[PDB]
Length: 116
Image 1: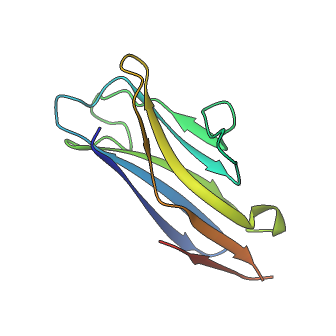
Image 2: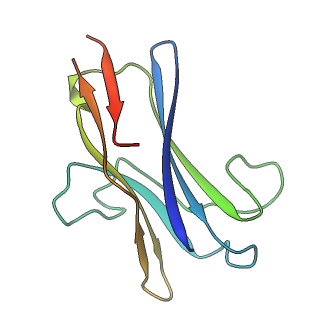
């Protein structure tokens, strides 16, 4: 794990929040990715909106040669989704964390995404 990048895509009423861990090709294993909303210092898999440990066989979505992806999908954005989000990842064995930058969704009955 070197670093985590954050992105977003949308179509119709649906918004996808995307976290991407970049890593060496031989260091694809042994970390969990997760996305947290409005935590103050306790972002973990247990406090996350979504977590994922990816198995690296062919035919599985999110599996890259030097990257791994987590996608959290909001089918319809409501006021519940307004707030500040962060992508994180954690390796079990070595203890290391990586954090992404903070970004925000603001419900306005439309929405803006900022900080990406």
